[PDB]
Image 1 (cartoon, helix red, strand yellow):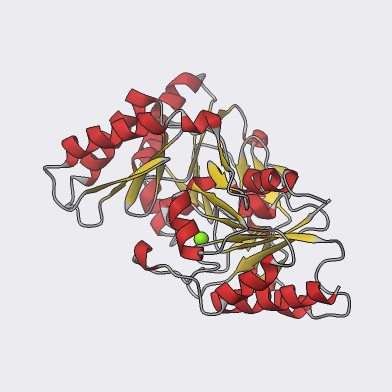
Image 2 (cartoon, helix red, strand yellow):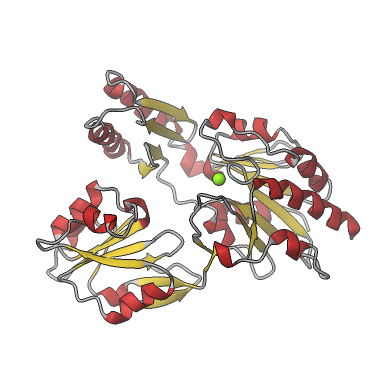
Length: 386
Ligand SMILES: [Mg+2]
């Protein structure tokens, strides 16, 4: 395995996203590749020829398929890893079945495992210094003038199982108000632009909704990803389709947002899960959309590359000044933004009790969403200082 240092190669085992790697036994994964994974805290295991099937091998490591990588030189492995929702499936082409393997469900195919990279450099959330404590040291948190970025759910707002029941954590409104008088603020969210705007309820700042595909400036200028916007009518049609197809089956919900269809199947019986999936993959094929899985949801999104780092970099390019970013996030999508804050930027991760001590690119930690309101207040006070 080639080592990539706080970066992302072509094929990358990413500890932040990947808790284990399941190797096909026929592969000869060197002791050097397993040791590489051992230093970054990633478990290994083998499945395959008459041995364990991928999902079983994953169960022995106490790791969900959504957090596991499979590496397989055979078709059965690739396919079984595909129907089991594995996060990353690397096909190893040793018999020139690159096309076959990718038809099976390989996310990507390599000839030799030394083409696979392992991300190094991230620390585990445990290990990180506290943001509040750093903010109050002699030299403060930032040397240069900042622009501050917030994820909404899990960061500014306490996690809730009812999406509609997400509200600003106590004190976070007065805090954002103070800070907003002091520097540019931006809240990021996967919710529609209107929803997050209403829930923060604070004007004269940047709102980025629908996964950064559309934002509002302080002056109220609307901005939208042009290429992504073309898929808006496409998605309304998939939603219309999916509602007729899955309407007969109770416990299955089709939720339509401006840049996505989400199909909730928490209350769906066994064997409509495969049927809920089959319909979304039909919607996929038919409309050239992008499917991604939640825990009990399947989502269709515009087939346009984008992440939270690109939102951040874009918003920054439009800020007046060389403005240094401070970024606060709660989960996995926020790792894209930690990675591009630059040599003076401050990436902060909000810890939860059930988060499991993930590896992260963030430099600091805030203990819960409650401290985020506290951090915001003191930041506004430290900037008023200078
Ligand atoms: Mg969140």
